[PDB]
């Protein structure tokens, strides 16, 4: 018996816009890349902005019936109130292709990059800047007329953590007070989009949901993992419905809105231990050492985590999608295995009743992996950066067969799947 998925299930791949499109000259990343800040690698990416017609054909060729990608706001508004029709018609064009070829799109309105001019005004740190976000949404409601699935922000907490708490990404800030004010503004921004789009669209949000484990059995550490889990995951998502989001000193009041679906981005698990330092909110995080074999960034592979992530996320009573799941290796055999084992768990989730409607593999093709540059290869499709040649890997075909047939067959389960509980 093959592992069967529902007919309407989505088997797609995902990309952003700064990572694959080339020369995105108007966003904050491009800027810091160019001056050599951090941003310490630059891009012209996969030059998808030129080759999109081919990438879509290739995509249609492998048998994927869905594509998750994002619209670059800085392209539609290079500067203050200067709209751009070229960018508009081009994305509009990309959308048509997808539809005429039967690929269900899922569009992300914001995926880590913002227009430089917007950031110069302080970005989402300053609530007044939300008027700019509003203009963007109004214009994008026209651009997406054929699309059904929209997600406002891609991983808002990772966005907040990297650029405001950790100083790892633009604007390079290390401030708990500010990081929380930004999160509250992201929640307002989401509420603003939902209000403007929910009519004609299904408006969701995309959350990175790591599996957070205690570094030990001691209650001191168990309490610490729950706290960290609530702080990085549930308080932010709770706020969408409750309207309250607790900061360091304040509790921000935002209007209650909704999300028509929650996209779950799942990669690995983290271990948390208790600390005395309030600056670190009283806990230290490290990557969980679960699998003996590590990933290119040294992450563990923990297939069961995706089931747990979906389970925890179903608490909101909204349909779920795995909007991202992938692996960076130079060993594609490991990728086929990774994909299959995660799908076995995505399948058991469906079996246990969870409302999961799709799976998007993180990355149709290798691409710009932010601060880490081009070294990590998450792609089903290899990309030659000198030529821009797309060379599909074995995984691209295996996954292609799966998406096309809506099932994982015997041969594959036995070769790569997990034995126990079969499925």
Image (cartoon, helix red, strand yellow):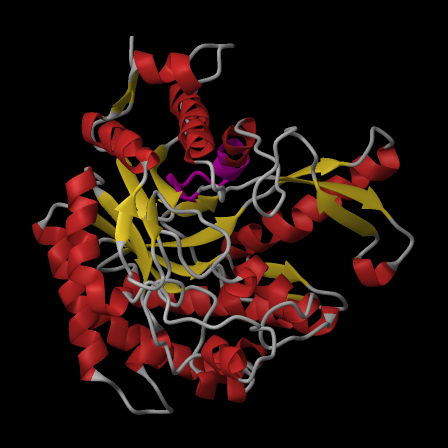
Please state the horizontal and vertical placement of residue 157, each as a whole percent of the image.
58, 58
**Picture coordinates of residue 343 (x, y %)?**
40, 27
Membership of 62 in magenta stretch: no
**Is 170 situated left or right of 401 in this image?**
right
Q: Which residues are magenta?
A: 310-324
The quarter of the image holding the C terminus is top left
In the image, is 419 to the left or to the right of 88?
right
Of residues 385 and 346, the one drawn nearer to the viewer in this rendering: 385
Q: Residue furthest left?
A: 100
- Where 213 sits versus 79, above or below? above
Which of these two is toward me, 47 or 304?
A: 47
Residue 105 place in picture, x, y as percent? 24, 52
- Left or right: where 179 falls relative to 51: right
Q: Residue at x 37, y 60 (%)?
A: 16
Q: Examine the image and state in which quarter residue 198 appears.
A: bottom left
Asked whether 2 or 277 is in front, the reply is: 2
x 31%, y 12%: residue: 410
Task: Give the total of numbered labels.
Answer: 0
Instruction: Pinpoint residue 85: horizontal percent, then vertical percent.
Output: 18, 82
Quarter-wise, where is residue 108 in the image? bottom left
- Whether residue 21 is visible to the viewer of this picture, yes or no, is yes
Q: Pick the residue in front: 145 or 208.
A: 208
Q: Is residue 253 visible?
A: no
Where's the N terminus, which quadrant? Answer: top left
- At x 49%, y 75%, the residue is 29
Task: Residue at the far front: name it.
Answer: 386
């Amino acid at each position: 018996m093959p592992l069967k998925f529902p007919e309407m299930f989505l088997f797609g791949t995902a990309t952003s816009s700064h990572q694959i499109e080339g020369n995105n000259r108007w966003n904050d990343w491009w800027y810091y890349e160019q001056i050599g800040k951090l941003p310490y690698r630059s891009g012209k990416a996969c030059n998808h902005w030129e080759l999109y017609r081919d990438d879509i054909q290739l995509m249609t060729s492998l048998g994927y019936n869905a594509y998750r990608f994002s619209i670059e706001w800085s392209r539609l508004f290079p500067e203050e109130n200067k709209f751009n029709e070229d960018a508009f018609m081009k994305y509009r064009e990309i959308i048509d292709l997808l539809l005429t070829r039967g690929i269900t799109p899922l569009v992300t309105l914001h995926h880590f990059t913002s227009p430089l001019w917007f950031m110069k005004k302080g970005g989402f740190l300053r609530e007044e800047n939300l008027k700019h976000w509003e203009k963007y949404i109004e214009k994008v409601a026209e651009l997406l007329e054929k699309v059904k699935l929209v997600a406002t922000f891609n991983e808002p907490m990772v966005y907040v953590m990297m650029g405001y708490l950790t100083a790892y990404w633009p604007p390079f800030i290390r401030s708990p007070f500010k990081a929380f004010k930004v999160a509250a503004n992201l929640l307002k921004a989401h509420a603003i989009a939902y209000e403007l789009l929910h009519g004609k669209f299904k408006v969701g949000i995309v959350k990175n949901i790591p599996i957070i484990l205690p570094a030990s059995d001691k209650e001191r550490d168990r309490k610490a993992a729950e706290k960290a889990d609530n702080l990085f995951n549930w308080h932010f998502l709770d706020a969408i419905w409750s309207g309250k989001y607790r900061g360091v000193f304040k509790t921000y009041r935002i209007p209650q809105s909704d999300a028509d679906f929650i996209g779950v981005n799942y990669y690995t698990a983290s271990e948390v231990r208790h600390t005395w330092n309030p600056l670190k909110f009283f806990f230290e995080v490290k990557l969980a050492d679960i699998s003996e074999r590590k990933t290119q960034m040294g992450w563990s592979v923990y297939p069961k985590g995706i089931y747990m992530a979906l389970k925890k996320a179903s608490r909101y009573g909204r349909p779920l999608y795995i909007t991202e799941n992938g692996i960076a290796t130079l060993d594609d055999e490991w990728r086929v295995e990774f994909i299959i084992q995660h799908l076995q768990y995505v399948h058991k989730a469906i079996e246990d009743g969870l409302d999961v409607r799709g799976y998007f593999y993180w990355s149709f093709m290798d691409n710009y992996e932010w601060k880490e540059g081009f070294g990590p290869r998450f792609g089903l499709v290899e990309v030659d950066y000198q030529t821009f040649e797309r060379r599909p890997r074995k995984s691209a075909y295996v996954y292609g067969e799966i998406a096309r047939s809506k099932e994982i067959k015997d041969e594959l389960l036995k070769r790569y799947g997990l034995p126990e509980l079969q499925l």
